[PDB]
Amino acid sequence: THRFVQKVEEMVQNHMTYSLQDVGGDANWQLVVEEGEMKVYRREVEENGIVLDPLKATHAVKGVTGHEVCNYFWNVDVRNDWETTIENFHVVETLADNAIIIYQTHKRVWPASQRDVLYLSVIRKIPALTENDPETWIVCNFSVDHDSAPLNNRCVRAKINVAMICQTLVSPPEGNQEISRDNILCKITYVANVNPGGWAPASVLRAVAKREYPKFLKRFTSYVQEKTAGKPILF
Ligand SMILES: O=S(=O)(CCO)c1ccc(-c2ccc(C3CCCC3)c([C@H]3C[C@H]3c3ccccn3)c2)cc1
Image 1: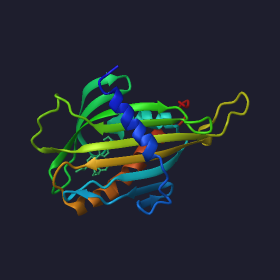
Image 2 (image 1 turned 90 degrees about the horizontal axis):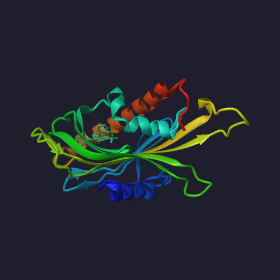
Image 3 (image 1 turned 120 degrees about the horizontal axis):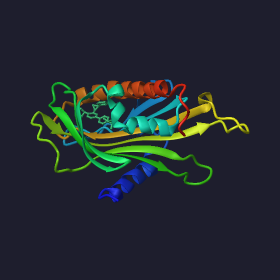
Image 4 (image 1 turned 180 degrees about the horizontal axis):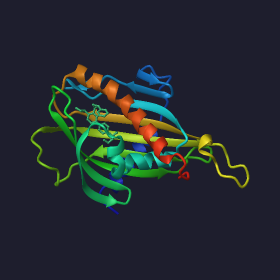
């Protein structure tokens, strides 16, 4: 259907295989911030003195479904309502109704150069592995090469591999009666592997990650709750 179908499959399947694992029991992940059910972990990793620190967070959001969370995360039309670190954004290519390529710039983090990013953003539903397991909605955003990448001399090109992975638990329907948002919970695993693509001071990037990832998860999840309240559920 498009030239990135196989790459998309590999990237999604890699998150399904490796990103969903629990890390509460795993001393190799450092728990850096906890705010209720929001648990943010990282590993301290540098390659050539540049911070790569894999980030992984879990959260549990009442009253929204994974399909809703993923749609709001993927939909570029609502990006401005919840993003706080983007300066500019351009849709570079549409590949499918569920997959686009995006160019964006982030606000400068002093004293490093501003960063830009060029990535494929795809939204997929993954069927239950067995009839015991939940279905998964996943958004994966991962860097790719493209010819219609802008010249932007202020920016160093970062590379990313991010996934927002959601499983939704509900009270079953009681005969002919809908499920209430009161009885729905969206379990989130969010992972972010960012390569700043060049020099940046490690302590500054680590301090920024520690602040901004929790702020993002809080703001974004609250936004989804706020926008879906009193609207019919989209499972
Ligand atoms: O979840 S998404 O796919 C949503 C679509 O945007 C996502 C989230 C985060 C990033 C990102 C990009 C650049 C940086 C660094 C690299 C050197 C200088 C800036 C960081 C580190 C600094 C951390 C951070 C966390 C949250 C928001 C912004 N900043 C993060 C990209 C995409």
